[PDB]
Each structure stands twice: as structure tokens, then as C-alpha cells.
Length: 10
Length: 10
Length: 229
Length: 229
Ligand SMILES: *CC(=O)NCC1CCN(S(=O)(=O)c2ccc(Cl)cc2)CC1
Ligand SMILES: *CC(=O)NCC1CCN(S(=O)(=O)c2ccc(Cl)cc2)CC1
Ligand SMILES: [Cl-]
Ligand SMILES: [Cl-]
Ligand SMILES: [Mg+2]
Ligand SMILES: [Mg+2]
Ligand SMILES: [Mg+2]
Ligand SMILES: [Mg+2]
Ligand SMILES: [Mg+2]
Ligand SMILES: [Mg+2]
View 1 (cartoon, each protein chain N blue to C red):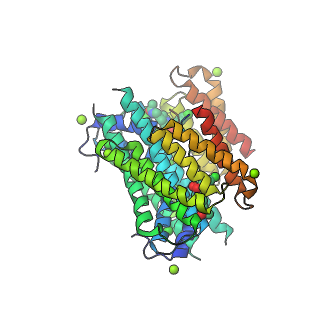
View 2 (view 1 turned 60 degrees about the vertical axis):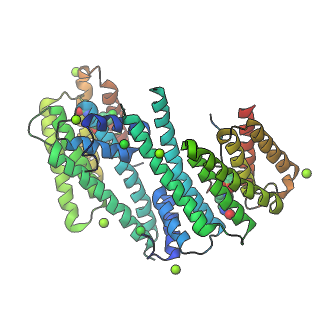
């Protein structure tokens, strides 16, 4: 696991 | 489901 | 071509890197370049060629089906225009494959394996064109597909054991042609069932280095038969 | 541009079709064309723009990381050459986004929402360049990223509730910048924890139309903190 950034939604 | 054809392998 | 200055072995190497990176357009481009060097492809190289272009055209077919579904579900020009843009792209990829097959890969000599695989590949990509074709072009595409599959079938029956994966995959894909493109559900069920039954009858012909591929196709044959019955 | 002759509304429509078809390069192309008409983007249109380009550059970053890993794991020119080809492509997409942001989207007027989102977007795509940059360009890219994130942070703290999704997503992405690009693990943990704690303290400010987005980012903040501790 690396750092999680903002995902895509809708 | 539609008909299944040859898949990709390796 | 854009790959003309690159050494064949570097092209093969890079297609393998692109497969690892899931860059299937690049992978397809590298393999086209390899094919254009004019030498025959090994089994591993044929798999690279097959995997790359099937991945490209698979994404295009899936896109086309979504847009076609939306188009018919609304039956402005936007959906039809965008569907034709994807369809034109898809046809361009199929023409590229079929051109490589005619200009370089399909020959009278060489392996039965190699000769069956390229004729199957010619059958598939005509079938992909047939999926999006209409009218004064449709039945002509359907017959080029049938004709290529049939030649591959004759050779495979004569020269390959009935569990050979190319022979099985070809038979699976011809039966899909029958059921979806030719609208011959009987021919489809009859080819698929024969192929599966002859495979089990000569199950002892499984190869040490391809039996996982063989048994996968046999299951997919049974999946299609369950669906079709 | 190739979209200059198409009406803005048709461009928006087609970007939505392309999203449905998972054609994110097309989707990005349509949205660029929409942006170049010179009018402001609504919230829904900003999401289309964001989703399209993040999908494009996401596939490129994932490809680059596979090839970089292979490159270092072997430390011929093929791996380095192919990695630079993907890297050059990735930089070209980031430049396209950053150019759209400067030429068209980033303004002094308009929504706080819109102004924060574009500065966050500028921060992200400089961060993506910073991931593949070296030397006399790296620290200059890092500072353009930090500078854009910081301006977005000042505005968001002044003008948005602490549960606003743009404010949260910005803070999440700045903290990822701190931890991965700036190598400031303390600043990362301190920003993420503050952002999460202030979000819970003013939990009542959740919006009816975006609370699912807000609570998702809050969880991702907690995921990063668990990872980093
Ligand atoms: C060894 C060789 O000649 N080529 C590898 C080929 C890849 C494509 N197949 S296939 O499309 O017939 C097929 C068959 C079975 C499975 Cl599981 C996948 C693909 C022929 C061999
Ligand atoms: C309404 C609006 O201005 N735009 C929609 C934006 C899409 C991009 N985000 S974000 O990248 O900040 C984000 C935040 C939260 C989640 Cl779950 C995904 C993306 C801002 C709003
Ligand atoms: Cl179009
Ligand atoms: Cl290259
Ligand atoms: Mg050579
Ligand atoms: Mg057409
Ligand atoms: Mg027997
Ligand atoms: Mg207009
Ligand atoms: Mg470079
Ligand atoms: Mg409170």
C-alpha cells in the first residue's frame, strides 16, 4: 500500500 | 450473458 | 512504420514490457513492428500479438456495445455520431490486423499450429467487423469470416489432436460465429458439442505444456452449450 | 482544436457518453473542447473534467511505476527507453491539464468551490509531474505544487465548512503531497489528523447532496493515518 489520494466518484 | 469466445491467457 | 528503425528483438522485449504495464496499444504497436520485419513468429510471439490486439479491439467492442445500446434505447445526432467514431476506430484496428495477416503472416508453408492460428485470427477479426457491419458489406464480411474459419477447421481436423488449444479455441470461436453472426443456433450447438465430446474421447492427447489452456476452452464450450440450451 | 467546430452542449453530452463507455481519452478530449469555449464549468462539468483526466493520467502513472520498478530491479536500453516514452506521454497530459487551468479555468472571481477545486487540480498535476521529475526541474515542480495547494487551503479554510468535499479532498491530497513528494511525514500526519478532527467536530455541516463524498474522504484520511502510524 502507498498513500491514498482523492478517488474518482460519479 | 452473451456467448463466450476464446479468452486471453499468459 | 514508426517501428522500422527498432531491432526486432527490442520490439519483442518492449511488447513484453507493455504487457506487464497493461499498455496494450503500445504492445500492439510493438508487435506490428515485429511482424513487419518479415520473419515468422514463434508460439510465444503469436501469443503476444494475439493478446495485444484482442485487448485493444475488446475495449473498442465493449465501448461500441454500450453506445449502440444507448442509441437504440433512444429510438439529436450526438449518440449516433459518437458511436460511428468508435465504430470507425474499431474497423481501423480490424483492418490493421487483417492486413498484417495477409501481407505477412498467412502462408502456405510452416507449422499446422501457425497456419491454423492465423486463419482463426483472420476469422475472428472479420467476425468483429461483422458485428458492426450493415447491408452491402455485411454478408460479404460474414462469408470471409466463415471461409477463414472453415479452412482453419479442415487443417486442424487433419493435423492436430482434438485437445489442441488452437483447435479447441478455433472451434469455440467458429461456434460463436455460428450462433451470433450467422444465426445458426443448430450449427453452433452441433459444432460445440462435437468439439467437446471429441476432446473428452481423446482426453489422453492433452499436452504437458498446454493442458490448462485446453481444459479452459473445454469448459467454455460447456458454458456456451448450457447457455444455448 | 479538433473540437472547435462542435457545440459546447454536444461536447458535454459526448463526454457523458464516453464516461459511460469507459472511453476516458475521448472523454478528456471532449471536456478540453468544452473548456476551450471559454465559459465557466458547472459542478457536474468540473466532475466530468476531473474524472476524465484523472483516469487518463492514472493509467499512465500505474504504467510508469511498473516500468520504473522493472528498471531499478535491473540496476540493454529497452526498459529505460520504454519508461521514458510513457513518462514523456504522462508529462504531455499533465501539461495539457495545467495549460487548460492557466489559460481558461483559474480566475480571481467565481465560486469559492470553483476556485479551490482548480487550485487543487493544479496542485495534483504538478504533483504528478513531481513523481517523475529529476534535478534542476524537481524542486521547481515541488514548489509550484506546494504553492497551488497552499492557496487552495487558505481559501477553503476561509470560505468552506470543514466537511466540504473539495476542502477535504484538497486536504487529503496536500497531505499525500507532504508524505510522498516533500518527505515531511510529520506535516502529512499533522494535516491529515487536523482535517479529520475538524471534520468530526463540525460534523453537523455535512451537505444533503455531498455527504457520501465527505464521509468517504474522512475514511481515506483515517486510512492514511493508520498507514503512516
Ligand atoms: C503457441 C502458439 O502458436 N500460439 C499461442 C496462441 C495464442 C492464441 N491461441 S487461441 O487464441 O487459439 C487460444 C486458445 C486457448 C486459450 Cl485458453 C487462449 C487462446 C492459440 C495459441
Ligand atoms: C461540484 C464541483 O465543484 N465539482 C465536483 C468536484 C469533483 C472533484 N472533487 S475532488 O477531487 O475534490 C473529490 C472530493 C471528494 C471525492 Cl469522494 C472525490 C473527488 C471536488 C468536487
Ligand atoms: Cl464524435
Ligand atoms: Cl520505446
Ligand atoms: Mg534485428
Ligand atoms: Mg461506420
Ligand atoms: Mg478415448
Ligand atoms: Mg454552442
Ligand atoms: Mg522524460
Ligand atoms: Mg461539534
